[PDB]
Length: 144
Image (cartoon, rainbow, N blue to C red; front, side):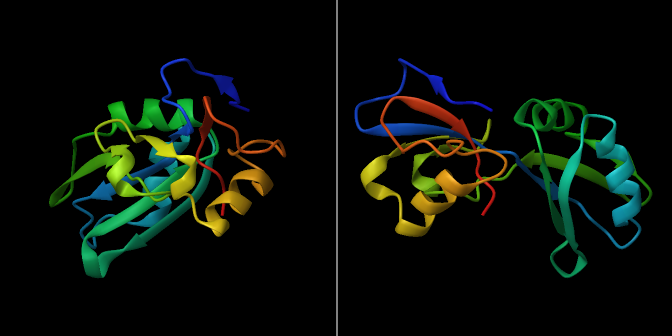
């Protein structure tokens, strides 16, 4: 688990690496079992939800490094009547604190909600692995 002292982090902040990818271009010809098999090449898929009414989906990998590999490989993939476009999702903490190009956030601890704080410490994957939230640490996205 990532619990990395990172001297690039400002005072009273943490850094969080998203494990979640946004999937764009999801027409009805693009189905969950096929996407799952595509992304399993890069590592174990923790969750995958498609919503064809919005032409999109969200895929979470157990590991941040697998998510990075999947994002670069699947960034623009012609498929049937569409192109699958894989980008980072930032679904944890304030979106104001994030680089959407890489799915990395630098979050002042004071802006975490109590729920955010609890998820960070209790997550099976990501988060602090049971340690307190303290400044200058980089973590992966917690399960909620």
